[PDB]
Structure formats: C-alpha cells, structure tokens
Image (cartoon, helix red, strand yellow):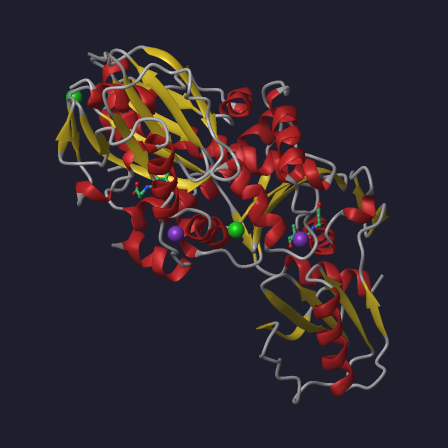
Amino acid sequence: MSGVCLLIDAGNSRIKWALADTGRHFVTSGAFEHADDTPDWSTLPAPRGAWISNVAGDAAAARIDALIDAHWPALPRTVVRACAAQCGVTNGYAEPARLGSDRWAGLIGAHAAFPGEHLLIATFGTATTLEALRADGRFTGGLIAPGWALMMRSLGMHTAQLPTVSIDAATSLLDELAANDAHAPFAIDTPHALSAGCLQAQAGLIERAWRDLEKAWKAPVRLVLSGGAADAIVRALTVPHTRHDTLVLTGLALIAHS
Amino acid sequence: VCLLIDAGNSRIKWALADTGRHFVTSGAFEHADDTPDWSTLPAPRGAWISNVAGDAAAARIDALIDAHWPALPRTVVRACAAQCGVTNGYAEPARLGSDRWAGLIGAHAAFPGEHLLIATFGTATTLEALRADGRFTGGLIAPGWALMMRSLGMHTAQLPTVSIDAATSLLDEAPFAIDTPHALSAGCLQAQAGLIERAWRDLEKAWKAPVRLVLSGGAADAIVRALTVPHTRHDTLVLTGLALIAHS
Ligand SMILES: CC(C)(CO)[C@@H](O)C(=O)NCCC(=O)O
Ligand SMILES: CC(C)(CO)[C@@H](O)C(=O)NCCC(=O)O
Ligand SMILES: [Cl-]
Ligand SMILES: [Cl-]
Ligand SMILES: [K+]
Ligand SMILES: [K+]
C-alpha cells in the first residue's frame, strides 16, 4: 500500500506541490507555471490520492486533473475547501465555505506548527493575506491586500507616466529591497520610489495589524510570514517575526493524513 | 488672473488665481466626457499646466483652453532642479511628477520653517519628504485605495471588485473581517494608513525632529479617520504651487 499523498496548492500565480508521507513531512516538492509547463512526476512513487487546493479558477482545475490522470489514472482525489471546522481549527468566517482554500490549509498548518500560541499569519503571494488564529484554533477573521508585485503592476497599468516593470525587472527590484538595511529612506528615482512605496505599504499593513491584534487579544501574538516577498519585507520590519514557508502544503498534508 | 491646471490620472483640477496666494474660483472634472464651466470666468492672462495624465490629456486641455481663449499663452510646468525655494533631490530632477513638484512648492510656502511629509491620495498614494530649508530629499509611490482594491478583483480568479463608495459603506457597517468584501476593503485601507504612519514615524526618527504630516488634495474620509498620527489637511497644495510658479 502507498504511504504517500500528493498535495497541490494552486494559486493565482503558480502551482506548488508536494508528496507527503506524514502530516508534517515531505518526500519531495516543487512548483510550476499555469501554461507551457509540467512537473517531473514520472520518477515519483505512486500516491494513494491527491489533495488539491485551487483558488485559480476552473481552467486551472481542469489542467491539474489532466496532469494527475496523465500519471495515475483514476487516482482518488479531494478538492480541498474551507469548512466549519477541521484539524483543530474552527472557521469564524460568516460563511465558512467562502474562505480561500489556501488560507484554510495554511490555518491548519499553522495550528499544528505552533501549538498553544496566538498567531497572525501573513502570506505573500498574488495577494497578501492575513489571518488571526487563536491558540484554541479559532480563526477569527482576516484581511486581504494586493501583494507587492501586483501593487507594482497596478501603478504602471493605471497611470500614464509610471512604468509597468517587467516580471524580470520586478524580481530584480524586489531582490534589491531584500539587500536593504533597516529603516531605509525614501527614494530619489521612479523605479525605486515604486518598489519602496509598495514594500512600505506591505510592511505597514503587517505591523499595524499585528499591534492591533496584540492590543485586542491582550496576549503575545506570533507573527508568521510566508512567501517570496518575505525576504524583502523582513528587512523593513521592526517587529518580531517567524518564517514558515510550508504552512499551506503542511495543512494539506494534515487534511490528507486525517 | 492666471488659469492653473492640475491634470492627474483620475481628474483635472483647476483654479483661477489673481496672485501667487489667492483663488477667484476653482473646481475639478473628469477627463471624459465632462468639461469645466468656464463660461462665467474672467479672461486669464495665461495658463500654467501640470499634466501627468499623458499626451492625450494635454490635447483635451489645449482644446478646452482654446475653446474659451484662443491662443491663450500657456506654460507646461515640469519639475526642475530648483524653483520657488525648493530644491529637487531626485537623481534626474525632471523625472519627478510635475504635480508632486508643484505640491512641494505649495507646501514650502504654506508651512514655512517646518519639516514636512506630504501625503497625496490620488490614483497613486505619494509621499514626499521636504526639509524646512526647501530640500526635497526623496519620496515613495504606492497604489491608491481604489487601485489596490481594483487590482485584486481584476487579477485573481475569486475576489470581487469593490469601489471606494462600497468599501466605505462596508467599513461604516474585531480587529479584522469575516467576509471577503470587508476583508479586502479593510486590508487595503489599513495598507494605506500603515504606509503613511510608518513613513511619518521613520522620518521623525531619521531627522531627529518634528515633522508635520500634510494630507494633500482630497483624501477619502475613511483614510483620514483611520490615521492615529497627527495630520494637517491642505486640499489645494498643487494648485497653490502652480500659482507661485505663475507669479514667479
Ligand atoms: C485571497 C486569495 C486570492 C489568496 O490566494 C485566495 O485565498 C482567495 O481567492 N480567497 C477567497 C476569498 C477569501 O478568502 O475571503
Ligand atoms: C505618481 C504620479 C502618478 C502621481 O500623480 C505622478 O506624480 C507621476 O506620474 N510621477 C512621475 C514619477 C515620479 O514622480 O517619480
Ligand atoms: Cl485561545
Ligand atoms: Cl491592476
Ligand atoms: K504607464
Ligand atoms: K475575480
């Protein structure tokens, strides 16, 4: 019998995956793009099923199915969705099912990773999302903002004079931010005014939300950060933080192995 | 009198000024398909135009001026190394937005002897740091509230598109949200407030001195209400800077 589960985290920007033998451990993992790209799965040991989080729409769903079937015909699979309660977490959304499935899995991962702690989970992807998670597993609410790269693109696409920086140039500007010292000053050129402005908006959101949460809950809150833009955001942060970049896949592993 | 035009990406603002410091009247309109009511205006001696909205807007503005005052003298205003007591710290001074430049000039005149942080809430949210001695030291550009919310609706599969009016009603409706529209309204608003607050605190820290935070042009009430730091509203900074340029 196979001891491994295939886990897929399809977001708006890319598709991440892992093969998990327990609720916490991955045998291997990787990522690919939505178009003209396919992962190396012909060397993988056959999984007992797939668990799929997809917030990228029906086209992506059909494409993921096509990839799974092209390797393991009729593999059992589960389309993961947020629900009222699962794996120690209870969903405080007014309509639990409307919470993003990625966010749900991340909550489950974080609950397991940091037992007994109040958390603010910050995940940097297409969007920047925040979730407040009590030590007793109650997800009490959250916030959504555009992510750094989306902010940058929005400015070029919706003003006459600001450049729409390319994917590669945006990556270069983000990497420059990740080389900055603390308390970076303002910029003296347009591309850096954009990069720093969008970064400071990210840092400002996270710090303001974290302080608000500690003050509301009257207890220490662990700020947990995830995602590509975290390296740059950490240079700007002054508040304590923890990095955990596998919360969503861990949550999927916990669901699969439950 | 001088006609002053502040054309941004979302709207064109204007004033009629009889000095560097006084407006006979003012107003605003959208690029298309609206137009200002200039029918009851005293004829101007010339126009001074800041335009960051592109060559097309520049054509609409010209046609508008020419329709009322054919071949009226006009001057396209651009950022430069130094003007009206302000010195431009940009590496390439002319690349600074002409609106930001005029706003700096207006701020230097309006709040003499003070270090300033100018926050302008338009299509983009901009910040400029301005020393009391007139040195513009640098700035930041982020998307505005509406742009942030629209970007999420247009560039994700599942999120809705929420306007400022809609978000304002939702937020008037622990410490975060339990549904998607409120989550994005609040997330984007708190990014706006957090940006400004963090920048102001960091600037006072860096300069070891008080800094007046000036909120330039209009700004959604929800943004202003959210701020926990002191601030001063000046809704006509750019136009007042244009009046100074025109009378210089
Ligand atoms: C916010 C995103 C886009 C982040 O990937 C995703 O979690 C999503 O589509 N969520 C649905 C709306 C919500 O979580 O309130
Ligand atoms: C940032 C905006 C769009 C604000 O209107 C405008 O000032 C502009 O196009 N600026 C040019 C780039 C800069 O000021 O660095
Ligand atoms: Cl608790
Ligand atoms: Cl956009
Ligand atoms: K552009
Ligand atoms: K959408």
